[PDB]
Each structure stands twice: as C-alpha cells, then as structure tokens.
Amino acid sequence: SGDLNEELVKAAANGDVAKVEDLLKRPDVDVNGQCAGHTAMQAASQNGHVDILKLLLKQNVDVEAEDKDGDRAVHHAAFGDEGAVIEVLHRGSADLNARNKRRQTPLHIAVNKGHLQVVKTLLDFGCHPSLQDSEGDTPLHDAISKKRDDILAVLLEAGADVTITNNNGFNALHHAALRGNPSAMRVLLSKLPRPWIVDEKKDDGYTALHLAALNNHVEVAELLVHQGNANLDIQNVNQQTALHLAVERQHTQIVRLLVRAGAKLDIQDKDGDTPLHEALRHHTLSQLRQLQDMQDVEKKSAASIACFLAANGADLSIRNKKGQSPLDLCPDPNLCKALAKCHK
C-alpha cells in the first residue's frame, strides 16, 4: 500500500509526530517503505525532526538503508543543519563513515553544504576527517572549493590531513593555490604538521608556489613566501622556478614579490634559459607580431620585467643551449641600452 508509505514519509518530512504515531500503530504500515525511493528515516533526518526519528528508531527500522544514490540517513542529515540528528543516528548505531555512490562521507556533504554544526558534531563523534571521494577529494579539498573558511579551520583542528592528494595529484595546499584561495591558504599554513610540507611537489614537480605564480594569485603567493617560508628556488620537472613561470605569463606583481623576497635570478630551465631570457624573448615576439601585422592584409610589460630583472642583478651573459645570451634574444637596441644602464 504505497498510499500509506507516502503518508508516513510525508508526515515524517513535515514533522507530524501525531500522524506518524498513529501510522506506526497499524499493521499495514511499512516503517521501511519507500515513497519515490525516499524513506521516512531519510525524510526526518534531512528535515531535522529528531522526535520523529526517535519514534522510528523504536520500530526496528533499517538504519543503513541507501537510496538510488547510496545516501543513507546520515547523508540526508548532512543536507541539514541539525546536529541533534547526528547524535540520534549515532546512538542508533548508524555508521557515520558510510559512502554513497560518489564515495562521499556525511562529512563531505556537510562541508559542501556549509553546515558548520553538523560538521563539528560529526567530527566530535570520531568520524574520519580525511577520507576520499570518487575524485580523490577530501573534506579539506571540498572546504577549499566551496570557500568554507570556518569549516576548513574546524576540520584542521580535528586533524584533517593536508598531504593527501586528489586523483589530479593536488594536496590541500596545491589545491588552494590553483583555486586562488588566500584565506584558506592562511589557515592551512597555520596548521602544517611539518614545515617542509610547504615545498612538497606534485608529480610534475610543481609546488604550491609554482601554481600560485603561474595563475597570478598574488596574496596566495605572499602567504606562501612570507607565512610559509616557501623555498623560492625549487624547480619543477621542466627545471623552471616559480620566477620562470611568473615571467612567462607576464605576472609583474609575482615577479616583484619573488625578486624582492630574494629569488635567485640566473637559474636555467631545461632549454638553458633564465627568467631574463624569457622576458626578452616575449618582448621580441611581440615586436615580431606587430611588424607582421603591419605587413599583412604587452611588449611594454615584457620590457619592464626585463629591466627589473637587470636592475636587481640578473646576469646579462648567461648562454642557453642554443648558445645565445639574453641580449641575443633582444634585437631592440634601445632595450639593450636600457638593460645595460640599469645594471651593476
């Protein structure tokens, strides 16, 4: 009798404790019935109706019952902001670590939906703070993605692990640096289990500081440098430093930050190029494309970066594998004159 299941589930969703009581007094009422795949336990858990949940628990209900997505009562409670539901389900022996089809724990959902009290109640009951979902993402990753800064701090107090990498190979710091999340990075850097975690490399050799420089995240990069004491001169697999990546993408504020912080300037990449090489190359290529468009039918910024590097001590003579010095990549005579003038 799907009508009676519908009535039970709807009363539970709405909080009609009287109606639920009268229904449970009947022999033709299924306490595990599903109306549109939704049980009364899931309804009452999602809507916060602790008293209805307690009556259901009296009736030997199946507590570990999934829906079509693998969501149990605990997962539906995480769609709400009532920690009391977590306490009742935990007293009822529900598994607070259960995975749905996407392998999300209730903690994952609570994080994603920004429900601080339920996140904290889960953590206080001892749920594991760093499990991984189908995409490899931990609750810390989620908290960074959805900009839940208070939840991120709470997770880190419960011992959520910054080192676990998602399927894409990003740990919590890498992920905050890709997303350009300064306030998440500030908390993360306050909670490092060991200092050198700031310099941990992805498989491609990218550190968090590489990611922040490459994507022009100035505050993230300031935090890494000055709050995390990030090593400025680490080289990715391509042997590029963060200063190489900032010059390649013409992120002048990142250039300034790295140089003023003391970044080495003459490190060479796989091709033998220094940052100065690459700034001059970009200048010349802009000039070439200008003269090519004029003869058919951004160069200021590159010049400015090159002069900054020179003024701060960049070697003008280092030779790459093709044997060419930085000046050999700059045919512009005026720019060469400017580089020599603001040097030594």
Image: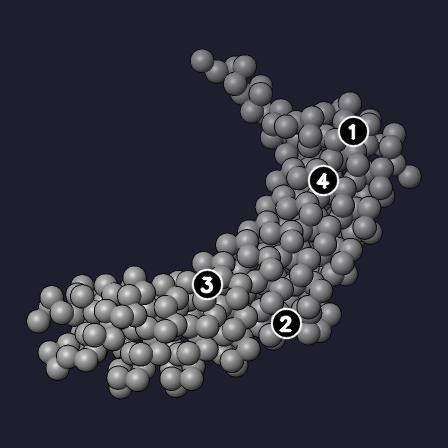
Disc 2 residue type (three-letter): Glu
Would residue 326 be visible to someone looking at this image? yes
Residue contact between numbered discs 4 and 2, judged by CB atoms under 8 Å: no
- Alpha-carbon span between mark 2 and mark 1: 54 Å
Residue nearest the observer in this picture, 118 or 60: 60
Residue contact between numbered discs 3 and 2, judged by CB atoms under 8 Å: no
In the image, which is nearer the foreground, mark 4 or mark 3? Answer: 3
Report the residue marked by disc 2: 157
Q: Earlier in the sequence, mark 4 or mark 1?
A: 4
Disc 2 on helix, strand or loop?
A: helix
| 225 left or right, relative to 207 | right
Disc 3 on helix, strand or loop?
A: loop
Check the picture and name the quadrant holding the N terminus. Answer: bottom left
In the image, which is nearer the foreground, mark 3 or mark 2? Answer: 3
Residue 253: image tag:
4
- Alpha-carbon span between mark 3 and mark 1: 64 Å
- Alpha-carbon span between mark 4 and mark 1: 23 Å
Q: Earlier in the sequence, mark 2 or mark 1?
A: 2
Would residue 327 be visible to someone looking at this image? no
Residue 331 point in image, percent of width and height: 70, 27
Report the residue marked by disc 1: 336
Disc 4 residue type (three-letter): Gln
Residue 195 point in image, percent of width and height: 73, 70
Residue drawn at x 76%, y 45% is 257
Residue drawn at x 71%, y 56% is 224
Residue 336 in which image quadrant = top right
- Alpha-carbon span between mark 4 and mark 2: 33 Å
- Alpha-carbon span between mark 3 and mark 2: 20 Å
Q: Earlier in the sequence, mark 3 or mark 1?
A: 3
Report the residue marked by disc 3: 81
Residue contact between numbered discs 4 and 1, judged by CB atoms under 8 Å: no
Residue 14 in which image quadrant = bottom left
